[PDB]
Image (tube, rainbow, N blue to C red):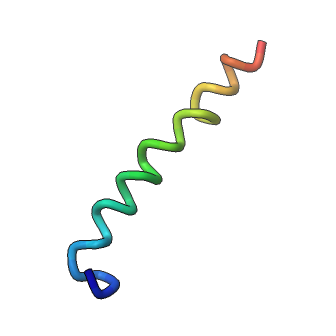
């Protein structure tokens, strides 16, 4: 922890994961 100090990963992962919702929306919209 200490903004860079590992923390980066865990967060980026949350982001990288979350994205799906919209990534798929464009199909999972009809």
| Left or right of residue 1: residue 25 | right
Residue 7 place in picture, x, y as percent = 29, 72
Q: Is residue 25 above or below residue 28?
A: below
| Left or right of residue 20: residue 25 | right
| Left or right of residue 30: residue 4 | left
Q: Quadrant of residue 4?
A: bottom left
The furthest residue to the left: 6
Q: Is residue 17 above or below residue 30?
A: below
Q: Is residue 17 above or below residue 26?
A: below
Quadrant in which the N terminus appears: bottom left
Q: Residue at x 69, y 25 (%)?
A: 26
Q: Residue at x 38, y 59 (%)?
A: 12
Quadrant in which the C terminus appears: top right
The furthest residue to the front: 1
Q: Quadrant of residue 28?
A: top right
Label total for image:
0
Q: Residue at x 64, y 35 (%)?
A: 22
């Amino acid at each position: 922890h200490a903004e860079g100090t590992f923390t980066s990963d865990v967060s980026s992962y949350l982001e990288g994961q979350a994205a799906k919702e919209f990534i798929a929306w464009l199909v999972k919209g009809r």
